[PDB]
Length: 21
Length: 56
Ligand SMILES: [Zn+2]
Ligand SMILES: [Zn+2]
Image 1 (cartoon, rainbow over the protein chains, first blue to last red):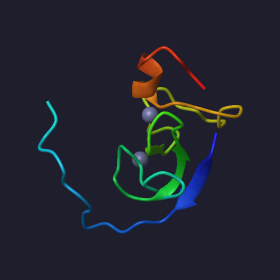
Image 2: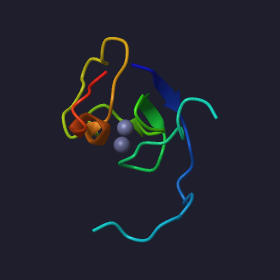
Image 3: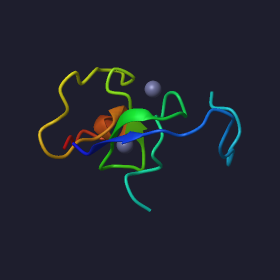
Protein backbone atom coordinates (compact mmCIF):
# COMPACT_ATOMS: atom_id res chain seq x y z
CA UNK A 1 0.00 0.00 0.00
CA UNK A 2 0.97 3.66 -0.45
CA UNK A 3 2.22 4.65 3.01
CA UNK A 4 3.78 8.11 2.96
CA UNK A 5 5.74 9.86 5.72
CA UNK A 6 3.85 13.10 6.33
CA UNK A 7 4.49 15.64 9.10
CA UNK A 8 1.49 17.88 9.76
CA UNK A 9 1.05 20.28 12.68
CA UNK A 10 -0.82 19.95 15.98
CA UNK A 11 -3.45 22.67 16.41
CA UNK A 12 -6.39 21.62 14.26
CA UNK A 13 -7.56 21.30 10.68
CA UNK A 14 -11.11 21.19 9.34
CA UNK A 15 -14.49 20.57 10.97
CA UNK A 16 -17.13 19.87 8.26
CA UNK A 17 -19.61 17.81 10.28
CA UNK A 18 -20.24 17.59 14.03
CA UNK A 19 -19.23 14.98 16.61
CA UNK A 20 -19.53 11.33 15.59
CA UNK A 21 -21.78 9.02 17.62
CA UNK B 1 -4.67 16.27 -4.21
CA UNK B 2 -1.98 13.67 -3.59
CA UNK B 3 -1.28 11.00 -0.97
CA UNK B 4 -4.73 11.31 0.65
CA UNK B 5 -5.28 14.11 3.19
CA UNK B 6 -1.79 13.27 4.49
CA UNK B 7 -3.15 12.75 8.01
CA UNK B 8 -3.83 9.79 10.30
CA UNK B 9 -7.58 9.16 10.52
CA UNK B 10 -6.97 8.34 14.20
CA UNK B 11 -4.58 11.13 15.31
CA UNK B 12 -5.34 13.90 12.83
CA UNK B 13 -1.58 14.48 12.90
CA UNK B 14 1.29 13.30 10.71
CA UNK B 15 3.98 10.63 10.69
CA UNK B 16 4.20 7.52 8.52
CA UNK B 17 0.67 6.72 7.42
CA UNK B 18 -0.87 4.32 4.91
CA UNK B 19 -3.19 5.79 2.30
CA UNK B 20 -6.49 4.02 1.67
CA UNK B 21 -7.58 3.17 -1.88
CA UNK B 22 -11.22 3.31 -0.86
CA UNK B 23 -10.99 6.80 0.62
CA UNK B 24 -8.64 9.80 1.21
CA UNK B 25 -7.55 8.50 4.63
CA UNK B 26 -4.15 7.51 6.01
CA UNK B 27 -3.29 5.37 9.09
CA UNK B 28 -0.33 4.92 11.45
CA UNK B 29 -0.32 1.18 10.71
CA UNK B 30 -0.87 0.19 14.32
CA UNK B 31 -3.43 3.00 14.52
CA UNK B 32 -5.66 0.71 12.50
CA UNK B 33 -8.23 -1.53 14.17
CA UNK B 34 -6.04 -4.39 12.89
CA UNK B 35 -2.34 -3.44 12.76
CA UNK B 36 -0.43 -3.84 9.55
CA UNK B 37 3.10 -4.19 10.98
CA UNK B 38 4.12 -4.88 7.41
CA UNK B 39 2.35 -2.75 4.84
CA UNK B 40 -0.13 -4.55 2.50
CA UNK B 41 0.88 -6.05 -0.84
CA UNK B 42 -0.15 -3.56 -3.50
CA UNK B 43 -3.51 -1.94 -2.79
CA UNK B 44 -5.26 -1.61 0.58
CA UNK B 45 -8.45 -0.39 2.22
CA UNK B 46 -9.15 0.96 5.69
CA UNK B 47 -11.41 -0.77 8.23
CA UNK B 48 -14.49 1.02 6.84
CA UNK B 49 -13.86 0.45 3.13
CA UNK B 50 -12.92 -3.02 4.31
CA UNK B 51 -16.29 -3.60 5.93
CA UNK B 52 -17.66 -3.17 2.42
CA UNK B 53 -16.16 -6.65 1.91
CA UNK B 54 -13.78 -5.70 -0.90
CA UNK B 55 -10.18 -5.55 0.38
CA UNK B 56 -7.27 -4.32 -1.75
ZN1 LIG C 1 -2.29 7.70 14.36
ZN1 LIG D 1 -10.99 3.82 3.38
